[PDB]
Image 1 (cartoon, rainbow, N blue to C red):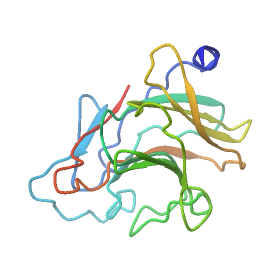
Image 2: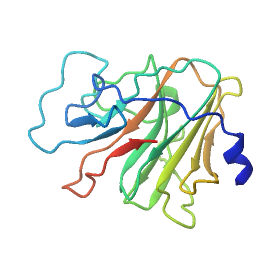
Image 3: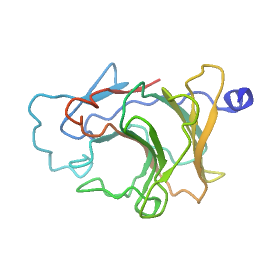
Image 4: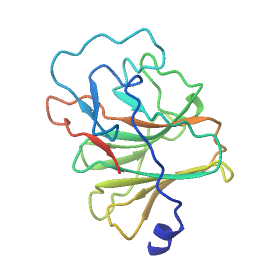
Length: 193
């Protein structure tokens, strides 16, 4: 676990793109914090760059080649999804979280079920396994065609959770789904480290 941590490249400098965010979301802290603003959900704009059904947002930064690593603090947020979305993938309407349609995601449900959104009709449940992760690390390598996820809760260690190995298309955008607030039960923010 100590090796993984050191083998990772410098932390990617990312910022949430406000123009792509679902209308219920608000971006703050110099683009490093995003959460649902429970006031009066306004209608989505006419720009296809903005998610209108998925309560998500992408980073300003597009990735096309090389290796990249970034971390996201999720804390005790019970429901979220993280990964990347292909630049050519649709962002409007109900989205289908499968690689074939441009989404490569790892998500959490009920605050305890970690699942990989593999090419299938049902996500693959993974092992927590010991303690609820509070920070997720994402490693993207175009040369190796992989997107891997790690439990990055421990400052000096990384525990593998899952990895997509099929060749990845380019470019892609780091993707973050905050999900519906679930009657105030899932109001926690997603934060870029």
